Image (cartoon, coloured by chain):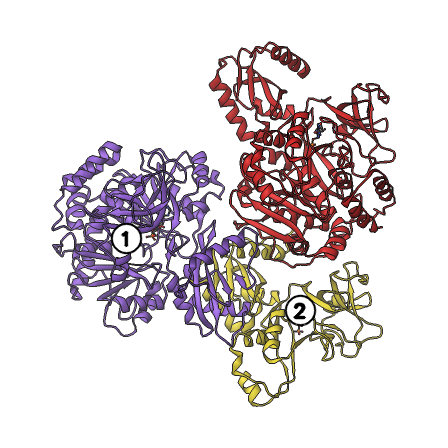
Chain colours: A red, B purple, C yellow
Amino acid sequence: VQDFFRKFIEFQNSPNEKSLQEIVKLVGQLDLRRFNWVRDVFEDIHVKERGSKTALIWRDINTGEEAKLSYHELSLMSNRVLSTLRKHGLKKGDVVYLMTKVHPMHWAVFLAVIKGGFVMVPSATNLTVAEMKYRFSDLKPSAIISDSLRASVMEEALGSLKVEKFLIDGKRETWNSLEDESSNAEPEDTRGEDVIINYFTSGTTGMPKRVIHTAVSYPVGSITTASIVGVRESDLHLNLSATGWAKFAWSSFFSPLLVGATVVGINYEGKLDTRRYLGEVENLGVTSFCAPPTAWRQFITLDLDQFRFERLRSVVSAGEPLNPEVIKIWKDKFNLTIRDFYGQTETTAMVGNFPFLKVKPGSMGKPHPLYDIRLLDDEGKEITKPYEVGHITVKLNPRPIGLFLGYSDEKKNMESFREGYYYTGDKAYFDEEGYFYFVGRGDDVIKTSDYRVGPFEVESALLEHPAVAEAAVVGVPDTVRWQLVKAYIVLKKGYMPSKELAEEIREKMKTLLSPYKVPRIIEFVDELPRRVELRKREEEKRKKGEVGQNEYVF
Amino acid sequence: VQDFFRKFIEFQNSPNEKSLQEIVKLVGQLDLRRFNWVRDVFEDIHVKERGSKTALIWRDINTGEEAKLSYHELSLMSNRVLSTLRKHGLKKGDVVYLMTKVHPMHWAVFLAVIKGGFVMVPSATNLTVAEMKYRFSDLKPSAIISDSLRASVMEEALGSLKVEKFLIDGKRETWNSLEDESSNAEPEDTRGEDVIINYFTSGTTGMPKRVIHTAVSYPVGSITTASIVGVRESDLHLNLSATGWAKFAWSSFFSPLLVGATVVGINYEGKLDTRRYLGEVENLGVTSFCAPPTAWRQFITLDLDQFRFERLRSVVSAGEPLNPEVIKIWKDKFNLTIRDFYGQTETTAMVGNFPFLKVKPGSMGKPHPLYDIRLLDDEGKEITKPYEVGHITVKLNPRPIGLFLGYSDEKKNMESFREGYYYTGDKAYFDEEGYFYFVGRGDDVIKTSDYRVGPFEVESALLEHPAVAEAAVVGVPDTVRWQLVKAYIVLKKGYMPSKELAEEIREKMKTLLSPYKVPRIIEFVDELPKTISGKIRRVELRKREEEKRKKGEVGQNEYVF
Amino acid sequence: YLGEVENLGVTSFCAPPTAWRQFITLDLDQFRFERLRSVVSAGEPLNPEVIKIWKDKFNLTIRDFYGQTETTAMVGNFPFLKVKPGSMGKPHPLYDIRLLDDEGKEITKPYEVGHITVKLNPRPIGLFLGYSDEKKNMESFREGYYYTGDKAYFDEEGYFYFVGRGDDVIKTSDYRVGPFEVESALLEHPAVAEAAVVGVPDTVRWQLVKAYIVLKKGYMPSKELAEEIREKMKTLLSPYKVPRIIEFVDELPKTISGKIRRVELRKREEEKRKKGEVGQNEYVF
Ligand SMILES: CC(=O)OP(=O)(O)OC[C@H]1O[C@@H](n2cnc3c(N)ncnc32)[C@H](O)[C@@H]1O
Ligand SMILES: Nc1ncnc2c1ncn2[C@@H]1O[C@H](COP(=O)(O)O)[C@@H](O)[C@H]1O
Ligand SMILES: Nc1ncnc2c1ncn2[C@@H]1O[C@H](COP(=O)(O)O)[C@@H](O)[C@H]1O
């Protein structure tokens, strides 16, 4: 039944409770034994029925460069990619690292990979030589693809491992172009359970592990997302997110292209300019906008009488909680509710405020009916009481569609999947109306600025500084970024705790760690205690507005 | 006046800002009305004080040959040249083409020319019969001097012009030896402003024209070079450069022999063997080494744990920008900074990271105080604000010493010498500390692989193919060679765009043009973007290439070789 | 030659792609070709762009078609058959043409590459008796099939596309060339210790004969040496066989067997082409 998508697309143009349930039931009747979302959905529905609709409107707010691509031109451009890859001897299942800015050719490559049945490893543009070498140790690349802005970082992290390398913008010695081949390569007949994506995600214990997604988990899971988001074919849909993560796939790629919408993509280097980006949203007449609460928190501090947003109809958030006061300010002004919704790299959207659902501020809504979401207590017994906190879990019989295969780590599978549930390692409570409220991680995992961060990874990099004897990294409350990365450091004898030392250590960490990971606070202490108790101690200090004796804030 | 160079040579052994300024002032007080650098510096300082020190160590990495000359033997050998020339009736001012490989007899001839007040025309060994015929049309030779490897090319380009011909290595019918007359002929009492060198260089407008250098401009301007380079009397100094250009007179000849150092010269035919050349650098214990970024880029790709370079203390680059990453790799390994410096055939070194100057990567350093260097905007007003790009210019009242006399082309003088400034046609910005950063050409001049290339010259050669109606040659970014030569060609009615045609045209170009000039890319187009007047917008051909690069596409009739 | 074609009013013209490639570079408004109705090519692939130029001008399709010394024409664009460019057309029904895979099973799928073979029961008529060499017959005639040693794929309409040789055989300028023959002649030169002869991509002649040479101790890799070797080879070898390039190397990349990886010689050539660089002692004539 590909008639599913045609029914789905209509559901979107005016959804409701009842018609949702039909969509749900119809997914259960899909044949997903052999599936390939590009062939079966992109080409067979969208390129065929609306080949000359605008698939992408792109702009770089720094350079000025702009591009407009129809579903046709994009399909062609993607085939040139896939032809070029195949020409360099890329078989199905081969590993392809992808590290580029927001750019048409990114979508292009996405398509080429999904169509060609490759394993793509999205890599963000801010990843360091060190972090990239880690990745290569864990999974070896058959091919890598970059922009010219980050070619040297790939080149250096590689050293001299044999790979086929490719540039999306410009030439460089021993890098290849992507459009020198044919505008038609044939689909790879993928099984639905075949692997197409690996995502390195941070966890509490170790260095980052791979999350494994299939030719259906994201390409068909995204339904749940698209349905919560309320993205339509008519829409111009902008998702403010970066290139090497799930949320790009989630909303910059799959959710819009599922429903045949116009994707809007905006690239910027460096720090977000909230008043120019928001102006470009209006200037491009986006109608559906996904942005992370970090962005939203910055937007509401603007003078909001600069903007009309005549065209803007749907507004959405994901990745962190959405302060009730943010929701309210944006509503009072533009008469739109910012609908928060929930998921992980491991999943698609699992819980969410749908378009037709009454929003309760600072609630992520209620479960999407395609996921069997349960709050369990410490014994793993199901919670049936308001205002009782517990573990967010996903029931595995029957196995929801958008759920990853598992981790590349067998220990981590043993912890997460058990007694017939996948544990998200998130905590929540529900209320008297069954609305879910995020409480936090049961882990020590951190989320600064909509980036998941592993403590041991930062502790590790910290011991690389000669001064550092011991280290413990925790997250500390911050209204702007949800949490800050703080490091407790025990110093070697010889170092005296100074501002200039804290800085020197931080600057070192910047060469080893992605910026979001580099501690914003460094506190030197005589000894370490129980990352739990580091947090508890911070809390009692907050209530007396007192700094630590050698706590240095950046 | 001799005392100048003795003060200079000391400055070198330990230089700084302040003592540089003293040097500057002292040059301004030299009496250079009648001057001859061979007599007055080579002979009177070096041959006299260090006659039996090694002036030159030479080595051919192909043949294996090594040969060593002292300041004396070289002075003698050069006099035999000058005696031999004079014997064949060469008066002052007479034109002498010099086309040879790296070889002692090259230095010899340099000397003989400077001493005898002749006009030498350095000619490169990869110049074609066609290129050479062009040269002869523009400046008729009184004598020509070659190695045996390139005698045929001169013989053919000559046709049946009367000239005296000479071989530096081996026998050939109707070619003469240079060492057969007595090693005793006298200086020509040259005016300091008398012409001794002509360099054919490419411009953005036409066929290549002669840059005119005097008995002081290079022989004494090279101070600026020597000073940035940081070459001493103690040093064994090697310059990776070719015979027919100005970088040779710069670091292979003048800069070392000024300070009484030992010159190191290495000859190779064909492709540079990076591992063998670097091995020969180490093996000969060179101490000062100047190579171009092209070379440097290639060196850093080696496994560099093969080398110690225990004897190397100075490393320098010039001719194109020097990637910060090159500088870094070489430093981390051998604990030396590759010091970038800037200039052109028309000048000596004008801007440079001197020995004592903290290097900011991707900056060519600060201006040498013997040139009055100014960034001007398009309207010709002086820029005094950081991070604003403009034209690099040289203020002409008073006229700096290392600056050429002008071009042999009056149109090109009209464009370069304007309102009391000479325009280099290079663009740059300076920072808050007065460090200069290269932006690129404001011309359409091209720089492949540290060779300056003229568009019209390649466009001309392209019209020689019956199929070609018009042509527009621009450079395209390339990390290995700075720029690639691309040609846009409009075809005559009757011929159709094919790869096979593109090739046929390129192979033709190979017989007419030096290899560096032969387009690496050929694109057929229906028309070339023009202004209202009908003038080609080479600018917009470049812009178009850029937009195509940023969506990783090659063109619909672009053929890459 | 094309002036003489027109002047004699030829009506059917076979020429090889080498010739065709050269013709299309002319100014073709010099000719009418009043009398010419059929144009055909054989022996190497026929570039789609060549086909098109000649068509746009004279309104004729150059029909490529396929075969070997061992056979007659086995596959071809017949006059009544719609040409798909860069396809040698469909099999002649008087040959039983089969694509077989590596295991020797018959290919039943579009866009799958394999060996062009001739099925031997019954034995087609234009097929040679065999070679005068019984070893070479044992290689070419196997498990009921004569192998052409060419590789191809077919499409959904049964049109064949040439992929290349399974062999190390070379075709410069529509002349089939044996490596060992040239390697042998090269060891005749005192200086030559080892030799590997490969074909390198060339638009004009399809492939160039290039020689990799390892030198005996004593001789130094020079242009003058390369030439001296080449001029010797001119007295021994038919011109088409005389290497157009000679590259001296320290060693030839080899398998565990000692067999030359002409594979990796080609891959290396490719990476060097993309930087328009010659090898350290590669001499092009
Ligand atoms: C070296 C020489 O004599 O060159 P020459 O052939 O006369 O050409 C002169 C042109 O070289 C370029 N150039 C020279 N030095 C440079 C440097 N340090 N950084 C960047 N560009 C540099 C400029 O563009 C000049 O105008
Ligand atoms: N709407 C949300 N509210 C609160 N936490 C969220 C929300 N969305 C995502 N998260 C957190 O982010 C994690 C997933 O991060 P990532 O793998 O980067 O998408 C989840 O495990 C949650 O803890
Ligand atoms: N039309 C063609 N396209 C590609 N290769 C061809 C073609 N015709 C001949 N060849 C090659 O040339 C060989 C024939 O060699 P010969 O016996 O000299 O004609 C075949 O085995 C092919 O590999």
Q: Is residue B1 above or below residue B195?
A: above
Q: Which of the 4 image quadrants contains residue B512?
A: bottom left
The residue type indicated by label 2 comes to: Gly
Q: Which of the 4 image quadrants contains residue A207?
A: top right
Extreme bottom residue here? C8
Residue C148 spot, x, y in % from top left? 72, 69
Numbered label tally? 2
Q: Work out which quarter of the rendered image holds the N terminus of chain C and state it.
A: bottom right
Residue B348 spot, x, y in % from top left? 27, 48
Q: Which residue is mark 1?
A: B346
User: Is A319 left, or right, of C205 in this rendering?
Assistant: right
Q: CA distance from mark 1 to mark 2?
A: 54 Å
Q: Chain of mark 1?
A: B
Q: Which mark is residue B1?
A: none
Is label 1 within 8 A of ligand 1 (CB to nearest ligand atom)?
yes
Which of A536/A185 is in front? A536
Q: Is residue B465 visible?
A: yes
| Marks 1,2: beta carbons within 8 A | no
Which element is circle 1 on? loop
Which of B553/A406 is in front? B553
Q: Is residue B512 visible?
A: no
Q: Which residue is at 80% across, 43% downward?
A: A193
Q: Which residue is mark 2?
A: C86
Residue C204 spot, x, y in % from top left? 55, 70
Q: Are marks 1 and 2 on the same chain?
A: no
Which of A43/B494 is in front? A43
Which element is circle 2 on? loop
Q: Which of the 4 image quadrants contains residue B371?
A: top left
The residue type indicated by label 1 comes to: Glu
Q: Is residue B240 above or below residue C29?
A: above
